[PDB]
Length: 45
Length: 137
Image (cartoon, rainbow over all chains, first blue to last red):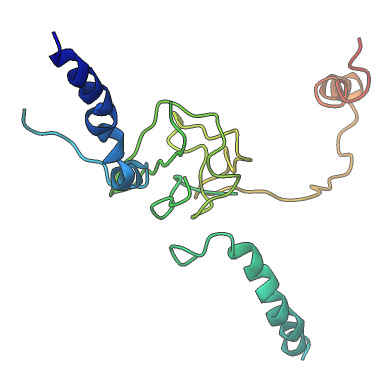
């Protein structure tokens, strides 16, 4: 019952820690994700 | 010695010609066979980088927006292989590739046989000259 007080504040503070980390690690990835790269072909599953 | 002193103003203007090259200085240094650039550093989707050659064949499904701001890098982007249209940023597209074309100027030929060509030449005039006079008809 009383756990939800500090649990809701902790889970909401992790939005930038978990979800936004996908786009936070893209700082150096997006520059590589930009079209000026070398393409490839997948020859094996 | 005209060419000797012509380069005096040309070499000084070569830097002015290089000023247009100063836009993209990467990759060292309009008819084209196939569209080719170096890495296309300039460039839904924002940037557009496509090249067809023995190395790094590229393809993009989207387009028709301004990434590059007109010419970029190798300056050759546009129609080749068909299938490929970069239009929106002032294209150098649909341009003659390496080929053999015979183009001359003023093929001057006077009248030869008017005997049976009286109304026969008029049929030739109705081909080319006719739409160039009164197209409203």
